[PDB]
Image (cartoon, grey):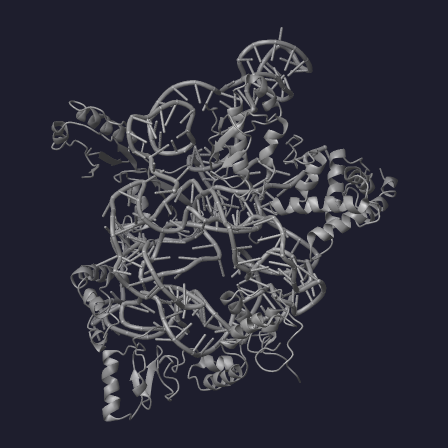
Amino acid sequence: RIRIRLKAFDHRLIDQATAEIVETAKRTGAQVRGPIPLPTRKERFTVLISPHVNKDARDQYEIRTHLRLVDIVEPTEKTVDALMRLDLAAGVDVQISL
Amino acid sequence: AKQSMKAREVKRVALADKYFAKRAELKAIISDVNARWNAVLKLQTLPRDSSPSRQRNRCRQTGRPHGFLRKFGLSRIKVREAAMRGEIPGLKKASW
Amino acid sequence: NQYYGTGRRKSSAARVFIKPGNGKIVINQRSLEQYFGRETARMVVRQPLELVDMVEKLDLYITVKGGGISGQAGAIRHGITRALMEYDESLRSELRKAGFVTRDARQVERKKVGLRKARRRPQFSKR
Amino acid sequence: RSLKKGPFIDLHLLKKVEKAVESGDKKPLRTWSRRSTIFPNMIGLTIAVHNGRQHVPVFVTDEMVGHKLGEFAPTRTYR
Amino acid sequence: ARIAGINIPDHKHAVIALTSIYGVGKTRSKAILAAAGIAEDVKISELSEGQIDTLRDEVAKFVVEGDLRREISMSIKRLMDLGCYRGLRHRRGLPVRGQRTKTNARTRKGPRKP
Amino acid sequence: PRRRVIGQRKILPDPKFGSELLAKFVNILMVDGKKSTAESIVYSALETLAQRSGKSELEAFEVALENVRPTVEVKSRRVGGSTYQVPVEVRPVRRNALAMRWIVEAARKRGDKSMALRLANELSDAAENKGTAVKKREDVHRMAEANKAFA
RNA sequence: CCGGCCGGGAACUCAAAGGAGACUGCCAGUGAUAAACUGGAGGAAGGUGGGGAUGACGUCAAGUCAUCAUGGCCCUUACGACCAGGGCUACACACGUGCUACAAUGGCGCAUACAAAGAGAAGCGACCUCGCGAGAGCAAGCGGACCUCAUAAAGUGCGUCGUAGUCCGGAUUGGAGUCUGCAACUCGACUCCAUGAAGUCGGAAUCGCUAGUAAUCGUGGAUCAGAAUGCCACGGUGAAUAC
């Protein structure tokens, strides 16, 4: 119970952020269904590269958005309580559903 | 880059929230078909300009109305100017 | 028991899993007729079954996702050919030799900036 | 043609309308705006609608109640 | 064996007979077909009275014939005293479209004689 | 168009007949990528030609193909300002394709209400060199017999 | 009752991190023994696997002192401040790009099947009812495989206009509305009619196009007080002439 969701755009950063928390709960937890890939967002933002006519000249910009889930089933309350106040993810927010 | 233009836009967006969200609410309360009478038509003291729907919300860097972008609140040229400088996370060149 | 088959073709994949039983094909818990199968590619689904013996070897449940009809037929054919090789490679030699395992990578090309379609540009301007 | 319920009249145009009703229809009201929608009691009072540079007087009758006030002020020009 | 008043509009399809009736163009035939769904193959000449009554109901509800003529006359009069110059644009037979009026823009108006 | 090669390409046949010739006929009879109706009209035409001819359908088909068969042609080069053409025996694949397209165009030369009826009637009366495309074959033959004066 | 809820599993497309796969391997031929060009266990991928970004010094006195910092300078009760109605939607000129048209495959009704792939909180709004309609009100659940468009059209057979201005072709002016800002008047776009004019495949023609490609059907984004013939991206059915 009490799953943890992360919304990041760097595959290595999200990989390490989900590979730290899972053993943070596994210090004294157990079970855990396992890592899940989760779907991703995709948006193609185009903008006129030239400031004067010639619409054909453009460029393609995109932003990634990865998601990671752990789905712990039966952990101990100690480690899930210890999850808070130990936040180290800088510039990226974590999503938790009560 | 008209500074009187930018002053008008700044003051209208400043008055786009303090003078709004309550006059429109009053109208919506009195806009019901059940009797609406001449009160709603006689309560037209609003300039009808401070409403955000009828307000451009121009770009606030060099005052170019063209290419207004909701995602960044900028114009195309300055998006190129700043994004290429980095400092905007998550933005990489797109290909597929 | 099951036979290994996924059948990727033209954005269509069909889980061909064959069990002992009748040679009838059940598509979406339904037969081909009341599935309204007299549409395009009405006979191509039995071409792979036309040459090989039916007897009592094939009974399969199939789900197909993606594509139109040629996509569906290609998915069926690729999945059944992938499930077919349980009988050693003796069959697969002629299966390839006859083009029965043909997988074509002729997917859609992306739309290009400046051209309103895959390869059509604006009609050339005045001289 | 189009539109919905709730005919409107400008508060300033309402002031002018009251002036024409009480003081009399001496001359057509040079209505600077065109936003006002005609009420049936207007029939008999002439007003002038500003199409952008001149206030065009309106043709008032009893049978175009369901007609827009701005129509009677033509906008386009003919040689 | 009859529709509306006394006449002989027979020897044609139901939709053809409808569009042949003045007061019903092809657009009114489209409206009738959308509202009811009567088949287009049936022949008006010597058909069962039930479908005849159905077509009568389809055609009688909305404005046709003499009502159409009086409404065209009223529209012409109102266009004469409309108050908008586009009223005279339509009344003069000039194309209200505003496209090229130099030549052959009066095709819908009709004949021209010396 | 000058560096490429020819791979002798082949596309989907009709499984009932399973012939490359009938495959090419049905695949050139295709328009805008239409499969159900096109093949339906093809089979309608085949059954109607068998019914009207009375003989075996496939041998009647072969007899029709033999009837429409042309022999020779030339190519326009514009060498000396006058018709200066070397009569070249056209490729058997190209000759077959041209005969196919002449049959298809002869079918196309009408504007009849029903495509099935028009196709059946014209191909059936062209099966015995008395229909529509045989006039085109004779015209092409008349285009020959005179281009050999210059070689 | 077609509750994947159990014990769930790998043979599951799917859902993202990483490793292999192809490099002309090795033989035979044409080849100076050089590089290259012809086949075979590979063609599930063979000859840069197919597509995208990556555009060398430079020619164009080209758009940008109206985006911007000025170079030499300048308007100066400001060459500004404002409030309402008005210009880019219009219109007696030639041109171009784009859209349904020339039918019998289009308006016909019915037992009526499979789309990848997005936007979603000045937002998406499953309970009922009716509207020739735009939709009209209680409208749940929601920053997400939760709650809106998967119903895909592409078809089986009933028959039609079974030949023409035709049941094809639906460019007009006024009669009642959907959300409009305060209200639709060169002036919001959409339904119901009176409306189907000209056109029976096209002047001396040019252009784009060598395999999912030219065409034929169906979806998201920008305004969003509001609708897309188009513009930026998608899934279908798929035609050879390269001596």
Q: Answer with left or right where residue D26 lies relative to residue F137.
A: left
Camera-side residue: D71 or D39? D39
Residue B54: x %, y % from top left = 28, 63
Does residue F31 appear anywhere in the picture? no
Residue F84: x %, y % from top left = 81, 42
* Quadrant location, the C terminus of chain F: top right
* Quadrant location, the N terminus of chain F: top right
Camera-side residue: G25 or G221? G221
Residue D15: x %, y % from top left = 22, 83
Q: Answer with left or right where residue B41 lies relative to residue A86.
A: right
Q: Answer with left or right where residue D11 lies relative to residue C113.
A: left
Does residue B35 appear anywhere in the picture? yes
- Quarter of the rendering containing residue B8: bottom left
Camera-side residue: A84 or E26? E26
Residue B69: x %, y % from top left = 31, 51
- Quarter of the rendering containing residue F146: top right
Against E27, residue G25 (above or below) is above
Q: Answer with left or right where residue E104 lies relative to residue G190.
A: right
Q: Residue at x 25, y 30 (%)?
A: A70
Against G110, residue A61 (above or below) is above
Q: Residue at x 73, y 44 (%)?
A: F47
Camera-side residue: B7 or A74? A74
Give the number of callouts: 0
